[PDB]
Image (cartoon, rainbow, N blue to C red):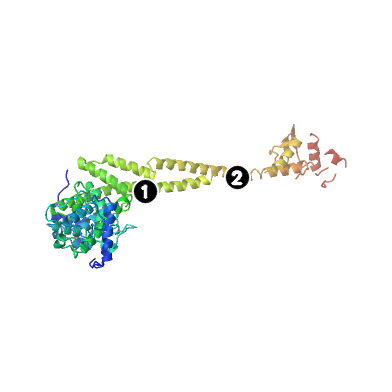
Amino acid sequence: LSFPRYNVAEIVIHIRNKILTGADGKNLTKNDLYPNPKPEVLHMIYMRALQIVYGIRLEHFYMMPVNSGVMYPHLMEGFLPFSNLVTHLDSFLPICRVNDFETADILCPKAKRTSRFLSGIINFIHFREACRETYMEFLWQYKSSADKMQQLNAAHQEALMKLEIPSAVYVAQLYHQVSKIEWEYECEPGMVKGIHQPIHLDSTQLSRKFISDYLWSLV
Amino acid sequence: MIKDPRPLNDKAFIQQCIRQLCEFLTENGYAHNVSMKSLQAPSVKDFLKIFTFLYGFLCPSYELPDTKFEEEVPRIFKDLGYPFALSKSSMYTVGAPHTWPHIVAALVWLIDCIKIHTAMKESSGEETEDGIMHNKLFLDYTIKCYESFMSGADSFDEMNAELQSKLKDLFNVDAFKLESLEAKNRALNEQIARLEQERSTANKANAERLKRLQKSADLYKDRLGLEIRFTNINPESPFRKAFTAT
């Protein structure tokens, strides 16, 4: 495979569609591409391409580096684009399957060469478009299941953080121990019944004191 | 930026431009002797050597065509974005008294370009307008896909696998690691509902057994006539055989 080679006419359409936006796209014609490409137009195109592929602000191409040391910063504006183009374009065109891009191509664009470079860029743009679809699908499968692990740590650490008589017994036990008796609760509707020997007293036909005395006489 | 903001008539201004030219050559290894004296009025020959040297920093291994230098040099300046025209004839007379001031200015402008370039070489985007986040990763993937596509395709499973692996690490999520906590956090919820049931059976088995031990306490207090927190010792008046003998 070498990449498909568009004719100038088709190159304008693809650039309008994918690279140049609004007024910049509208103004593009075959004329500023062939037979004498226009450096200013090509600069615009390469900058846009780089901004799309790498995410680079247009600003970044017009930046005056720190202790520059230049006499007249403002006489420098025409040169600035170039400096920043070169470095990125050396890396980017190989990716587009172009291996013979040279600074002359930025400074003084030739017809047949820039046509081939533009097709290289355009074809890569279509390919990544296809790659974007599948990447984004994968990036909503993993980041969505990351949301399902946020909620799975919300319900797990909350329910891990929630997990993170000595007066009535001794009174009721002394009765049982010192007397050595226990009631049967089958004491009819009135009588008293229990075990010590079996104790069986009527209580309707017996005094309270008689019952007390009979119980303590066995202790 | 036409206009000439530069006072090309000021001898001090030119001499200073000459000095920069001199300094840059001497300090960046120009192979030929230069000095303030030798740069007051260079020949076309020496000029062409100096220019070839300087432009060399922007176009490595540049050499000028053996003919039509009067056209090349100005064209080169134009393409670099030099705001002021260099006439075909000034090229023929570079070091002459009405020419050198204009040329040396151009050279000093060329030196600034070089300084700019030189700098943006030593000192050296993960969000995209399409909506791609982690662009460096996506680029890495797209590039690898393209190279494969380059050769044979039309599958990118090596790439998709590697991408999947990198996404696993970046997010720490697996179809297993998510599922593991799914039953792991469900396991303690039933256990919590079960620990709730112990504490719920502990409330009814306490309030019913304390209501049952009080009735037995009343039954012992009535039968034996003994209260602890005595009766029936022939009075039923409040107060064993030591109490019965009094």
| Residue B5 in view, yes or no | no
Name the residue at 28% across, 39% down.
B158
Name the residue at 34% across, 58% down.
A67
- In which quarter of the view is residue A208 placed? top right
- In which quarter of the view is residue B169 placed? top left
Residue at disc 2, secondary structure = helix
Name the residue at 45% across, 41% down.
B184
Subunit under mark 1:
A
Residue at disc 1, secondary structure = helix
Q: Nearer the viewer, residue B187 or A13?
A: A13
Q: Position of residue B126 (x, y in %)?
A: 33, 51
* Residue type pointed to by label 1: Ser
Q: Position of residue A146 (x, y in %)?
A: 39, 47
- In which quarter of the view is residue B243 placed? top right
Q: Position of residue A23 (x, y in %)?
A: 21, 63
Q: Position of residue B82 (x, y in %)?
A: 22, 61
Residue A52 marker:
none
**Going by the picture, which residue comes out furthest to the right?**
B246
Residue B204 marker:
2
Kindly identify which residue carries mark 1: A144
| Residue A149 in view, yes or no | yes
Subunit under mark 2:
B
Q: Is residue A139 left or right of residue A205?
A: left
Q: Nearer the viewer, residue A159 or A186?
A: A159
**Going by the picture, which residue comes out furthest to the front?**
B37
* Residue type pointed to by label 2: Lys
Q: CA distance from mark 2 to mark 1?
A: 46 Å
